[PDB]
Length: 255
Ligand SMILES: CCCCC/C=C/C/C=C\C/C=C\C/C=C\CCCC(=O)O
Image (tube, rainbow, N blue to C red; front, side, top):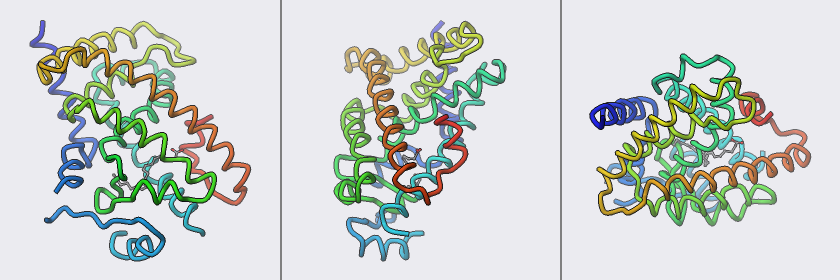
């Protein structure tokens, strides 16, 4: 019955709002247009005054900032996952496995909410780092964000809102096809119900948007592609920068 799917969609949106302090709705209000104006970093000097206004060479300081943020995001995504009905009843090992593989796919999904074609919000939306400035960073740091911007521009053309994204990131987490899953079936049973919830949500929220459900699911391919490209870039850094710390929580995820 659709009444149960709407209850599920409302539950997850409620938990999404409780778990993720910077929503897409707030991100868009900041990015578009007096109290919410970000400071804008587009070079080293603006970065210099930015570190003052908002708050080791430039590329590395930016890189570890990303690390700290990703860790914070993992923590938010973990909190959100525990609210997905059934998730915490799964085998403990499968819970770790689902988070291990799902966490970066969600990060890039939600990172798009903070992006437009020209740059990305930072520091809880207080700042805005331009795409060009990041693309101009020393090799191989200048290659990190561009694939993410490329995805975001197309993903954002779907015009999903937070209530759509709450169900969609839940679908990503409950993927029965992650390597090493000990009991696939209860995961798939949760995802099927999440998939039913998503389907009804997009049909009601986007009545004119034909086959949005199918297009959103095909986007899960771009997400996988971004991860593997990102993993390769990290292995270059581990050898180029033997003095540079990578956070152990992220180390364990990438293992
Ligand atoms: C919205 C809250 C404020 C965030 C402040 C952002 C600081 C860094 C700026 C841009 C990048 C944003 C997120 C990190 C993305 C990928 C992390 C790569 C490290 C890894 O996982 O291997």
